[PDB]
Length: 102
Length: 102
Ligand SMILES: [Zn+2]
Ligand SMILES: [Zn+2]
Ligand SMILES: [Zn+2]
Ligand SMILES: [Zn+2]
Image (cartoon, rainbow over all chains, first blue to last red; front, side):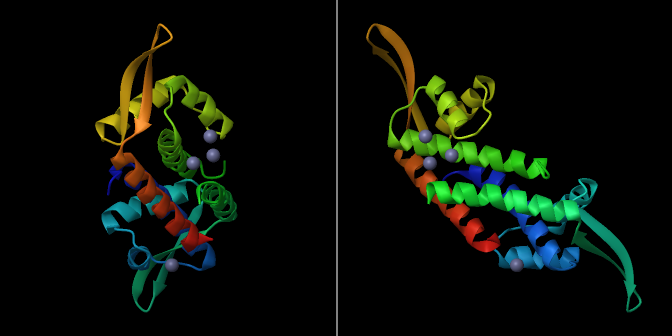
């Protein structure tokens, strides 16, 4: 990239937004988020993603639940009401900036 | 804001993009950038702005020159060819993320 600092800063925000958007549509496992983010073109390792997930729950924007499904313990994440509101606000900021420069 | 970490991350990118867009259109004084960024709705202090400006020059994306105009010495900033290309790349990343989540 010509502007690696922009890409670096912008990716953090992009990831955060994608996590919230996916977790508002439906419940998600961390492992699936890694694959899904990759499909959308973001290079993310579990080592980077899980701390983001935990932070989002700490921020009250996600909530996780322990589930035992098919003899296997798994954590699922979903958006809280605060998360859906955050998503609206974040999307709004994106849309505004998109409208302005494009 | 519901998601202050998103807003914080997103604002850095937004500012960076605005600096490059203004400095591609015309030459700018740092003091004027502060006012202009304020008009566009970004809280920026000289203490935050000048390090960003210096970083952009170090990255080869801006160039500054000491200029004496009307018996008065001033520093002006403008985008380099690399800066115009960075602006295109950054805008492109924005467009992509806009397409994805809207
Ligand atoms: Zn997706
Ligand atoms: Zn602009
Ligand atoms: Zn302007
Ligand atoms: Zn603006």
